[PDB]
Image (cartoon, rainbow over all chains, first blue to last red; front, top):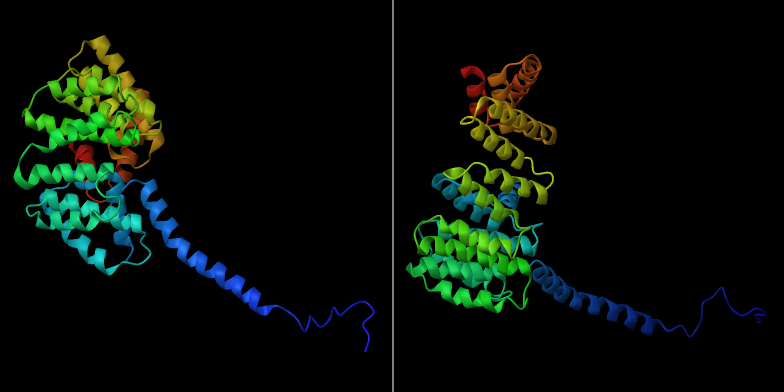
Length: 49
Length: 290
């Protein structure tokens, strides 16, 4: 079998799924951890209650 | 039921609990906690703690205040005791817990430590207002409180409407009726669309007219009409503006004043329609009495 223009229909046998899931999980946890800090600090300090 | 939340937040931003009778204040205190602990959804943290400090003040007003110490302990956790609300709250706590005046001095130098703008200007504006509230009770009563406000007012903070409004109230209570016009005019200047500063600025002119000469009476009642027409123009169901327009036009009774009398009578019968509650009893009496 030959592919003159490269193989663009089938994606790859060497796709890096784990790195993509690691990126998604890092973004998810960093959002979930930074949300309480910004919420409490800025909302309770800006109104000076 | 979030309608209770609407009522509580309206009382909050209006601070209407200050003007409550002890029976309705007790009712407020009783009905606060049930929603406070039951309807905990859709309510933000800032509103949570604002309701907590409203409950603190309600308890301090009320007879028992051990729950005041408990609530202050619960609310101390966030932003400690350096926020202006917390400073005022603990000053009141130390004033009422033992009926000792000492808090003032631990507040006094604090004001003298705020000159360097370590906090916002509203912070020590509020602290100045509270310490004047302390000192008017320290020396039980005098006209000098007005002088204190003026010396605190003129150099430091003209913009604050509340101070000029209290000056105008003190002038109207037993003082001159003329300076109150200037104070209310300033309060009108800061807050352009205040629709209750026009009712007061017309009532004060009406009171000034009742002891004046006939030409000055005519001028003052003309100005009262020209100032009450803006309370008409800024609100439809405003009771006091319509009542005042009707009363002064009835006192004059001219032909176009009679047109205004017909229109104001129709509008006061609209207000006294039973959609409004407990403002019908003060409109219908003025309508049917004379």
